[PDB]
Image (cartoon, rainbow, N blue to C red; front, top):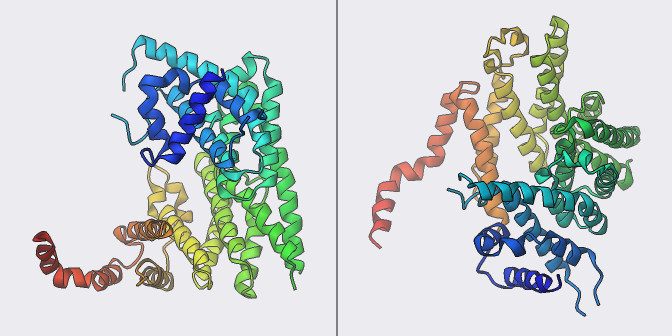
Length: 435
């Protein structure tokens, strides 16, 4: 009770202090066989995190670690297998009973306590984003069963406070996924969550719309920018996993971008978010059209929208800020692939009017960016910058293979940048082998 509390405090210390386990997941997995009983005392952990001390209180670093270890033990119990990277997975009768009983325990416990944890740690972006990895392991039917509506209401209260307090993309994405999970995975509660969600969206689409109007009518304040960016960020996070087309967000995103091209003075993060948001609006418009039985006029409406947006991304390659260029580039390579002739697979030849062949101008600009921004002359941030330039090239590579760009002009550039490997590689290879 306090005994299991000491073991968990020291387990959190051994993790943080030693360098013998880099990953909480791997530490938990390693102790799992021997210490499952301790590692699922979730009442003990939530107690440590929620109680006030008598003496010796936990540090902010230690609290952070305990939450991370707790979410790891919650996954391990729910999934009943080692974490990604330690895999190899058939369960005995007793392991399956333990999985069900564990799923039942952590669900009852965290439905009650997860709202209290979010409340207390609401301002801590890393902590809240970890805590919000928890409902995905819930046995959501229990919200009905335990006459537990009061606690669903409480989680939604606290998610609302999180989204309202925060702009970090990790936190917003955690909130977006948590609404997803609560919705379309149990009809009983689907309606209650749907109401809380659209109310949240309504309040943010109003704030976004008023701020867009503020900024464009306006000289322009620091407030005027913060308000647009901050509200747009929330809606962009959500627009990936929630169809927000009923709010015409593409319209106001389009104006923001059209203004940043024209008078050249739109802040980079507004442009990036505005591009992402527009893209998500277009993907969702596409799903409603595929699955529906769309008219001729329906197709030509979306086509005008997609042509105007391809044009905005083309133009945003010329923006001075390289995060803008990368975003525009990534979207160009997505959209040019999506609205390729691929679209007329699976008997869906109705969609021909939605097909887009990029012009020479565009293909040349999609060549330029690769030369300028994938292949550049010159810690932790640089292994991350590299994987992105990889993802950029790979996105571009798909367009080459299907002749959507000039496959020759591309390979020519791939020669030019591989030269020293084709000219000296054998000599460099053998030299290095004998050392």
